[PDB]
Amino acid sequence: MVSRSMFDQLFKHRNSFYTYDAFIAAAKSFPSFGTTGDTDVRKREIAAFFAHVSHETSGGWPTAPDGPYAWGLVYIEEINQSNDYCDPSTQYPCAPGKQYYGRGPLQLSWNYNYGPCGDALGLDLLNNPDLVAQDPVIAFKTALWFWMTPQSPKPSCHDVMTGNWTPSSADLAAGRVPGFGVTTNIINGGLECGKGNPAQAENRVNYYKDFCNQLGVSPGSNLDCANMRPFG
Image (tube, rainbow, N blue to C red; front, side, top):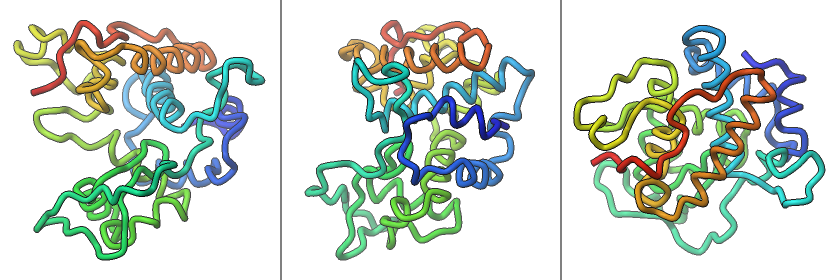
């Protein structure tokens, strides 16, 4: 998987909520994560997941010890907790008294994501969304759920990084060629790819390249997403 000492090197300044043991327990619920493909493909997948996590939870600053990519996994909850992040749903009804703001390593948000994520994990996250911010095993599981789960027309980020997604002719025409860039496109491409301001996407790439360097792997091809359109 990832050794404890390597986890503690990549995430040297993290919030101690996010324990290595909790990450390992979560990954055992998604056993193909980081175990798919040859050695370089596995390292790239792990670096890619951790890069996105770090970008979404970073407490870094430009003169921080160990540099601006060493401060991933500092944040648990979204700061502004005034909006409920509730879109009325008959399938995933918003629980009275609860809110669906961002929680965990990939900032799970909205009743319409807490619902299906919870169902897949066997946890009532729709009616107890605060679970994600209480229990680091659950927190990591919500992030791996997102990484590992297709949402047609989008493949899973896992499949993109491990050779299990082959683009259609339309994907290719749109610049969606397998690599790290497509994972940014899946996560938040409507805001960060295409003609969006490229700053956030370029930050994700910088974490990814740094983590690939530490793991001793080439980052591979197609890292940018400015030359690709978000999935329809």
